[PDB]
Amino acid sequence: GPELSGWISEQLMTGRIPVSDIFCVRQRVIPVYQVNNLEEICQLIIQAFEAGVDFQESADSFLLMLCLHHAYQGDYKLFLESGAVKYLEGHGFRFEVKKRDGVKRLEELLPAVGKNIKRTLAAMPEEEANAGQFLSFASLFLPKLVVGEKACLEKVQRQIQVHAEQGLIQYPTAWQSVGHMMVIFRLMRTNFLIKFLLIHQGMHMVAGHDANDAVISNSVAQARFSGLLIVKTVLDHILQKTERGVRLHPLARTAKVKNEVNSFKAALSSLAKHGEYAPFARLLNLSGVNNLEHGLFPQLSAIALGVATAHGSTLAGVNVGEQYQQLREAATEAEKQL
């Protein structure tokens, strides 16, 4: 019987159960701008992102201001002390507090270099939503972000109606347009920090009746093991459950597969070092996540599909070739003799 629940593969992946139990630097300075008109500045930030302004570098700073207004209510000392910053500080990030008074344009916050940013902001016209709504809407992208653009936006269109037919939150219809969704997709795809700050919040937040934080909570929970689902269902099928406990499938213990099983455990160990941040590894592009692709292990994919075929169930995203088809046929028969 295979580990169809998914508990063991989750515990192994997170790092709660060791890999050996079954199988046997430079910092980046980010400016934290201190202002009085935090609500006003954040409105000028949202408008710029709506317009499609690519701040590139200064993207982290202006996004960090939106998170301060909503999640930290304008408290700099509480933000610099929070667990989110504590993790970032030990993972190649440094937060420098810079005081700024009398700021009326985003050009006053921009660092000296990036000539197109001040030009695009100058051409912007002078004429609806809050910082929190922006953050919660961007969190709706996380579920299917790594999948593809069409798959991501479709999931975004579907979720919006779910949140509206339950009265949790209603977003401006100017956001529901293809163009603005694509602008936010491109931002979420390239900007690491926004993904992590939404993820850290979804992971560590006892919400609550705040509509935006509840949307972040659900979206972060939906994004768990995103882009690692195929390899998680494969690991679930290559795990044999006996009367004593859980053990590796006999077909993986053979001399022919031995080299691949060694590569798999080396990639599973790298993933498990991330602790609680392991389900979001592909989403966050963490160290050694690319070595954990389902395609890189076609012998383990053959044993996984074989065991599944015996039970009548299929594996979505698993395409076993002719070369490994022999191993698929042997795995089906071994599971049939129960």
Image: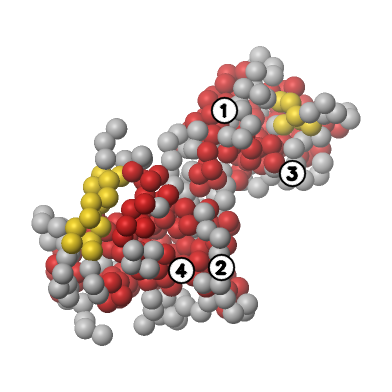
Numbered circles on residues, count? 4
Residue 143: image x %, image y %? 53, 57
Asked whether disc 1 touches disc 3, contact meaning CB atoms under 8 Å apart, the reply is no
Residue 282: image x %, image y %? 48, 45
Q: Is residue 106 visible?
A: yes
Q: Residue at x 51, y 47 (%)?
A: 280
Residue 92: image x %, image y %? 31, 40
Q: Identify the residue position indicated by label 1 in the image.
A: 264
Q: Residue at x 36, y 57 (%)?
A: 79
Q: Quadrant of the C terminus?
A: top right
Circle 2 packing at 10 Å, graded few (<14), some (14-19), many (20+), is few
Specify which label sits upstream in the sequence, 3 or 4. 3
Q: Identify the residue position indicated by label 3 in the image.
A: 5
Q: Identify the residue position indicated by label 4 in the image.
A: 137
Specify which label sits upstream in the sequence, 2 or 1. 2
Label 2: state its secondary structure: loop
Q: Residue at x 36, y 58 (%)?
A: 78
